[PDB]
Amino acid sequence: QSPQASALYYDEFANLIQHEKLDPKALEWVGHTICNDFQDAFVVDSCVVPEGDFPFPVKALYGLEEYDTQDGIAINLLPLLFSQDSPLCLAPYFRLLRLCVERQHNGNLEEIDGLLDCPIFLTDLEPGEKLESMSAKERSFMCSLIFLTLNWFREIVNAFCQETSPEMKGKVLTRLKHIVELQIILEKYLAVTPDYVPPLGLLLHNSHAFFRELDIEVFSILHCGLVTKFILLGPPELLFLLEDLSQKLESMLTFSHLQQRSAQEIVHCVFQLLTPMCNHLENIHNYFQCLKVQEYHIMSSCYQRLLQIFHGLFAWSGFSQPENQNLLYSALHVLSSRLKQGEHSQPLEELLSQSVHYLQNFHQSIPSFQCALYLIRLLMVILEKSQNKEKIASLARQFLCRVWPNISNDQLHALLCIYLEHTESILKAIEEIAGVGVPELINSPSSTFPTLTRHTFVVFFRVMMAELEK
C-alpha cells in the first residue's frame, strides 16, 4: 500500500539476491512471482493511445527504432503516474527481476533484452519553453516523470553494461545519449521551476543523494573509444561517468552501494578500470588542446577530473602500506609504458622518473587553472616517493606565469605554498616576488608575474608571510 515501504522491500531483497548465494529453489519460487508481476504491472500492449484524458500529447517516445515497431511490448509509465495521482517502485523491482534472472540462468537476459527496445508512453517532454508561464502541478508531474524515466534508464544501464554483445552496447550508447539529453531537459525544468522539488528517496544536492547511485561494473562503458563531435562514446557521456567515479572515490578514500564495498577493493578495481583505456582519452585530450565553445568547456572539465582521478588514486594512504604497492608497481608499469614498452623488471625510482616524464609533457595542453594545480599536486605526490624540488618549483612557476583566461583565492593559496616549499631558497623566492608586489601599483590599474590581480595580492601577501614565519 505504501510506496516508500514497497521500494525498501524491493531494495533490501535486491541486496539479498546480489550478495548471498542461497538455495536456488527459493529463487525459482520468487522468480515466477516477480517476473509475471512485473510483466502485468508496468508492461502493456504497444497500441499508440493509452487510456485516460490527459492535458498532454501522450505518445510512445525514446524507442531505438531498429527493433520491430509492430510488436506488443511497451511501458504504461505516464497513465500509471496520472492514475497514481505501483510506479515509484519500477527501478528497484527491475533491479530485483534482473538479479533473480542473473542468479537463475547465470546472466542470460534473452528474456529481458526486448525491454531496452521498447518506447515509454510519455508526454512530448523535449520542449519546456513553448508551455512556459503556466507553472502549475503540470511542472511537478513533468519533473518527477523525467526523474523516474532517468532512474529507470540508469538501472537499464546498470543491467546491460557488463554484456559483451556489440549491438547491445550500441543500444546502451543510444540510451546514454537519451540519458544526457533528458538530464539537460530536467536541469532546465528545475532551473525554470525554482523550489518545486520531488524528494523520491540545487543540481549538486539532486546529483548525489536523490538519484540512484550507479554500479562500478557500469564503468565497463569507459573501454569504448571517443567520437569527439568538433574536430573529426561522446564527450558529455564521458563527463557523466568521470563525475560519478570521481564523486564516489572522493567520499570513499578520504552512498550506500559504494560503502558496502571495502576501500582496498575499490582501489584494486579502479586500477584495471581506469588506466589502460583513460590514458587513450588523456592522449586524445592533449591532441584536442594542442589545436564550438560548449565542446571546449566539456573537454576541459573531463581533462580536470581525469587529473583529479589520477591524483586521488595515487594519493591513496594504503601505498604507505606495502601489500598494496604490488598493485602500485603494475600501475606505474602502465604510466612508464605509455611512452615505450619492452622495459621489464624496472626499479621503483626509474618508474617514478618514467611516469613523471610521461605526465610533465601535458603542461602546454591545460586550458584552465584547476587542471594545472591537480597535475602539480599529482606530480608532488608521485615525486615525494623517492632534488625534484626544482621540477615542482619550475612547474609551479610555469603555471603561475601563464595568462589563464576565473581563479579562486584558495586554489592560488595551494599553488603558492606548493611553489615556495619546493624552491631551493625561500628568502630569494620572497625578495623576487616582493620586487613584483611593487609593479602591480606602478603598472597595473596583471603585473610582471600574472595571477597577481588587486584581488590576488591578499593571498600572495598571506602565503609569503606564512612561508616566512614558518
Image (cartoon, grey):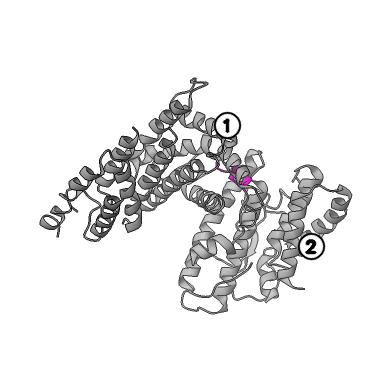
Disc 2 versus disc 1: distance between alpha carbons?
52 Å
The answer to whether 442 appears left or right of 178 in the picture is: left
Residue 326, numbered label:
1
The answer to whether 427 appears left or right of 327 in the picture is: left
The answer to whether 118 appears left or right of 392 in the picture is: right
Which one is in front, 437 or 141? 437
Q: Which residues are magenta?
A: 216-222
For label 1, the crowd category at 10 Å Cα-Cα, with few meaning under 14, some 14 to 19 and many 20 or more, is few
Q: Is residue 60 visible?
A: no
User: Residue 437: where, in percent of width, then height?
Assistant: 18, 53
> Label 1's element?
helix
User: Residue 249: where, in percent of width, then height?
Assistant: 54, 49
- On whether residue 336 falls in the magenta region, the answer is no
Mark 2 or 1: the one toward you: 1
Determine the residue positioned at 48% across, 20% down. 343
Determine the residue positioned at 66% across, 47% down. 160
Q: For the residue marked with disc 1, what is the amino acid?
A: Asn
| Location of the N terminus (image quadrant) | bottom right
User: Residue 381: where, in percent of width, then height?
Assistant: 43, 40
Q: Say above or below: 444 vs 89.
A: above
